[PDB]
Amino acid sequence: DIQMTQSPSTLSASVGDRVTITCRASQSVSTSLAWYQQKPGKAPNLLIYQASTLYRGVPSRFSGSGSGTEFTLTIGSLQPDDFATYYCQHYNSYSRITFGQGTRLEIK
Amino acid sequence: DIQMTQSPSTLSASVGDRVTITCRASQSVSTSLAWYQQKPGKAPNLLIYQASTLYRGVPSRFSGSGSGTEFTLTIGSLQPDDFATYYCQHYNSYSRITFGQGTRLEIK
Amino acid sequence: DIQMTQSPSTLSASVGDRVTITCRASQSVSTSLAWYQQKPGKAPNLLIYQASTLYRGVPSRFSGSGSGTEFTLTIGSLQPDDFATYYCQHYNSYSRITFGQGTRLEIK
Amino acid sequence: DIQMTQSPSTLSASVGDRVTITCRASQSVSTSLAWYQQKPGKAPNLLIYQASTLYRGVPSRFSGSGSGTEFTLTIGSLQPDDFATYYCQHYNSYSRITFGQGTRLEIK
Amino acid sequence: DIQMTQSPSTLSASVGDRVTITCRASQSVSTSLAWYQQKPGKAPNLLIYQASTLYRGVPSRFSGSGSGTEFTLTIGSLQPDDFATYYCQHYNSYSRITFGQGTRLEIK
Amino acid sequence: DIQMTQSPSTLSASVGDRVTITCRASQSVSTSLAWYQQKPGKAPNLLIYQASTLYRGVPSRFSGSGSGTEFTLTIGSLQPDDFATYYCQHYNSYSRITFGQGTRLEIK
Amino acid sequence: DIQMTQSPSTLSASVGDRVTITCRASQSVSTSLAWYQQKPGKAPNLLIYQASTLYRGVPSRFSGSGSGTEFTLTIGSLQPDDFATYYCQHYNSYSRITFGQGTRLEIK
Amino acid sequence: DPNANPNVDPNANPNVDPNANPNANPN
Amino acid sequence: QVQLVESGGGVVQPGRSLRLSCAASRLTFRNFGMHWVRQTPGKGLEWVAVIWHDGSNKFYADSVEGRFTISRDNSKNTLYLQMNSLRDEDTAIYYCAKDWGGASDRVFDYWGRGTLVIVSS
Amino acid sequence: QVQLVESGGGVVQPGRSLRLSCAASRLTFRNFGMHWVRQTPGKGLEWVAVIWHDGSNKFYADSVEGRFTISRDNSKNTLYLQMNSLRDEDTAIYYCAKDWGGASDRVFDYWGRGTLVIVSS
Amino acid sequence: QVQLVESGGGVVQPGRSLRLSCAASRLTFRNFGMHWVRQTPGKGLEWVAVIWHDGSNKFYADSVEGRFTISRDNSKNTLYLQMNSLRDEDTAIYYCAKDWGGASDRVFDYWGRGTLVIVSS
Amino acid sequence: QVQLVESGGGVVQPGRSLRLSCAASRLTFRNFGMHWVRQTPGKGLEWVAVIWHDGSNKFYADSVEGRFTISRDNSKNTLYLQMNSLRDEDTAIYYCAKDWGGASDRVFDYWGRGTLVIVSS
Amino acid sequence: QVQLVESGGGVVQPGRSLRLSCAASRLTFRNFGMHWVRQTPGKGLEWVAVIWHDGSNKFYADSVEGRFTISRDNSKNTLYLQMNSLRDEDTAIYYCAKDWGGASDRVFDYWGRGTLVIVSS
Amino acid sequence: QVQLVESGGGVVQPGRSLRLSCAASRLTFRNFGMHWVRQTPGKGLEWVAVIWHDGSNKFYADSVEGRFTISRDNSKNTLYLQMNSLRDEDTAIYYCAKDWGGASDRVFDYWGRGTLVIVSS
């Protein structure tokens, strides 16, 4: 099992700004990452897979980047409905699937 | 024996309508069926034999069709005299003659 | 031939109880099974045919079920007169007639 | 065709021991195999069918076992009358009936 | 799913020249590809399968080669009837079938 | 389908020598092959099936061997009558039956 | 093989104290180190892997540090149940798994 | 290397190949 | 009400012959095929044979194939089963039968009383 | 010489249902698996669904998972694809297909003419 | 007790015809399919042919396809196998057989005595 | 001795239909599936069609899919292959064949004589 | 549209067993591998187990190794995970999942609503 | 909760072979590579060997090359290691082990109880 650390734990931001979310792996996991956005009371939804590819039906304002141990989830234009909890997940070969702690986005 | 089951148990309709009565066989009986009409106070009379052939002297508004286990007696235009009890009777070879329960035709 | 195995060999119960007797076939017999009740000193009498149908004149407290190789005869409420030996007999096509061992119902 | 190979070709044995005769199929024959015992000058007699069932009238000291391609006939306690040539015969579906080469039993 | 990217999007040529159409995948598909020609107004037709084999009834001026992620469909001598849109399609194991964007050939 | 290529195309040999005909399948066909001998003007005759088993009535000088994609037909001692054209055939499951190009044996 | 030396062989301490047990490798093993505690009569159990990471279910009071050839286990507050034999075991790539001698921690 | 991972890579593809031969077996 | 009475039992040495009758009463005998059912002393039930309405076809259980001959005589309203080459396995109580007459169900409804046949010495 | 004719198109509101057919002619339909291929107005091709020869297994693209259900009628020599919960992304010409029949090549040889389905208001 | 006696043996030159009989006794011959089994001088056993109860279908081993014809006469209680274009490998003892009568067990129980056929010159 | 005699050949123009027959003799034709094998003038062999024993299933080579129809008449002991929309590639001598009868071996043993079919103008 | 419905929750003491179900709707369940994902009240996400399409292989996180059994019943269109020897750490919401289907992507798309399991006194 | 019970120990003479078993319970045995760790009476710990998940590759410590063999039977949920050319310096308590399953971490988590082997005379 592998420890995924994503920073910051909590980042407050307003509507329309540029917010980037990082996720750090304990070793190189190549590019077999994923990102999940969980709204309170609901199951998390898939956003990015392979750390750069946009999942079907997801708004284009979301973008993924990074490789190895450094990764970044970039939001092109934060929207009222975008505020939620973000989890970074990895599925590297010969390792078990683990998640991050989960960053929260707060208005203002 | 072979159980003769016909549906519906009771079907109400008004003069001038078209009604279809279906009889279900417990097992295949080829095309050796018959339909009888019992007006209360009278013994039933013959209408259809061989499941498709109109008897002699029966009004042509009566129609029968089907083979195997699904058979239908169809009345093209329901008439004031055509309210009575209808039975389906089979005479398949090597099986004994059985009758159904009998559908009631009730005015309006 | 097709061997018929019925279980249990002996099953004791008292008046008012509900018991189930099974019959297991070596190979599929579809629904071609029959259940016989033999009281001591007398020839067995027919109870069920077609593995589910009630024979004429038999009290409705008997019920049969099953298909393939697993079949069940159920007495809804045991009566003092229903204590006897029960046999399951198959008549599968192209296979010869065989009987089961014979389940015994013993009082108390 | 499915060519049967029964091994080994000849086992010498004395009265009272236990002998096992095998029959190997080139391809799966499920459980459809039969064992024949041919005493010299006579037509072979049936011993086992379905590779595990004992034919009627055969002494119980003969027993068969196995499925797939490895089938064994076992005589628990050999008797002086049980000295003969043994053939294994398959009757698998969609394949023609073939026989083994014939294992012999030799006294001492 | 593997996205299929083929280049160039539009390549213009005249009658008699030799042109090459490349198809690039995000991850290796071994040699499991195909090529399709769609003249405007009708359904596409099969040209190449297994990325190198010429389908039945196709003129031999068409040639396919490459393995892994880089593939090429080369027309040996352009003809007036080979002006159409070309789609490259993969059918790699454990991945769903996806087509390319579509390369068009324009006269002169 | 599976394309079959057999080499050499022509194999000249004399009486009493030993010849080897190879038949290479484009993809694995397990052990489902067949070897045919065609004398000029005659319908081809079966020699080997399952790539190693001798067909009934064929002289024992023919021998088949190999598995997977590489198969050989070897004539132990070529006889004056055995000068003809040879074809190899596959009948692998889920694939359509195809024949070879045809190896010719030429005297001297 | 890589010889693995740990010091001290025996170190006595009391409840509530803070103790280090060190282990030295004959050659660099990066951070591929593991640690085991063996209570008498029981198999050794995992405490630290990767020379710094805490295994699941291990109390936080144990801590490991070091890289290369010099490594150390630090127990913040020695507890009465922490009294056993401790081993240092490495799994460096291209080398076979070796163990230390085993520090014994003795009461008072 | 004796220390190579002796496991089965729990992230192997767990689904059915959708491109398996869907035809009938003509033989 | 239809009753079936059997007769012709007794004691026979192995290898001798024996004839069994199933004279019926008040049954439309000619329209119905008839079975013979054998109950061994071990309370097992075995089916023996069946003859069609006109006697056109017969079927025997393999345990009595070639040794048992069953014949039906419609005129005298009776059924016959003749036993040849008996042995220790044929000592049992023999019941007549009457197929229910359905299209495809081989079940017995009006059983006979039973006649006992003993093979011993 | 093997032609595929589809029908059942038209225009439907989002959220409604729609049935599509691929009645085939002169093809040995039962021995072949079939595919549905979608061509968007952007001239791109997407694979939709596949059904095996006997209907044992079906496979759908992720964009049509759970919304589309295909079935095959071997006796009637036709193929159905039922549409549920449509939306604006499904407005495209729908082609039939016939898998080439190779051992491991999922490639379509005999395409249909093409049926248009429009989703709008 | 069911005995099968075969006849018609002797010596014949290759290419000549020969007829074989399996006149049965005390068996209900009409209800049972029958088999011919050939035992070579090398003590091997080869199955030859089977005919159904009424002669509806026949099956032959590949070694006797088109040269051997088996026919059954239920009225006279006998079985016939007529051989044409004989050769040296058909010299063997020919055994009549009787299929056991099970649902799916094609196993011979009541064999005949045996008839020897010699093909030589 | 198993002889397969074909007929119905000749010369036709492209686009015309043509019927071939494979009247068999001395073979149990009903119990065997049969094949048609095509031998091109380039001396290469190509498989064409296979028909099951009772006509339940048919399989064709892709080069003759939808243009060739193979039907079997068990009563007349003959095999039919009717071609439609012929073209230049179909000039070859057509062989009948008989599947060996093995469990999993689709290998032809008793080939026919051969019928020459020419397509030209 | 594909909805995953979990059930079988409640409150249990440490050391007893508990059964969970993931009855699926409109998903082609047989063709897809499924996962169980646990979300602790501390808002952390922790993976539990995965079963392949037919159940050939199962992989567990070390936290539930030997405590949890994941079983799939394709016929009834549902997923089962049976819990044994629970403790305080297993107090969390349990989510069903469906693997996306990529060649090398282990990501979940169609999550279930979640079923709550509490281990306390 | 996943326990490894070793068996097959005792006292042996030098040079004689011996079989040991490591039958496991409730562990997903097929997915986990297993190890043998040897503990001498001098409290020294020596790793013996490792077998991969399916037995594809086996590695041994230098002290037991060519003398000890280790086999893994996933079907019966058990492990085997057989010793040959046994001698005094293998007098120890033998411990089974289960590799954790990490990407590059070769550590043991679930040890067995241990089975004692004595080499003496």
Image (spheres, coloured by chain):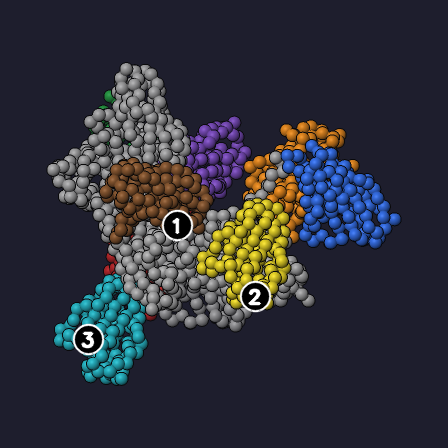
Chain colours: A yellow, B cyan, D purple, E brown, G blue, I red, K green, N orange
Q: Is residue K25 visible?
A: no
Residue A28: which quarter of the image? top right
The amino acid marked with disc number 3 is Gly
Labelled pair 1, 2 in contact (Cβ < 8 Å): no
Instruction: Identify the secondary structure beneath mark 2.
Output: loop
The amino acid marked with disc number 2 is Ser
Specify the subunit that label 3 lies on.
B
Q: Is residue I36 left or right of residue K18?
A: right
In front of the other: K39 or I49: K39
In front of the other: G108 or D89: G108
Q: Are marks 2 and 3 on the same chain?
A: no
Label 1 Cα crowd, 10 Å radius (few <14 / some 14-19 / many 20+)? many
Q: Is residue B43 left or right of residue D66?
A: left
Label 3, label 1: how many angstroms apart (C-alpha)? 56 Å
| Tag 2 residue | A14
Question: Is label 2 or label 3 in front?
Answer: 2
Q: Is residue K54 left or right of residue G78?
A: left
Residue B104 in the image: x percent, y percent? 28, 79
In front of the other: A24 or N106: A24
| Tag 3 residue | B76
Q: Quadrant of the C terminus of chain A?
A: bottom right
| Tag 1 residue | E98
Label 3 Cα crowd, 10 Å radius (few <14 / some 14-19 / many 20+)? some
Q: Residue at x 52, y 67 (%)?
A: A80
Question: Is label 3 or label 1 in front?
Answer: 1
The number of numbered discs placed on residues in the rendered structure image is 3
Residue N111 in the image: x percent, y percent? 68, 45
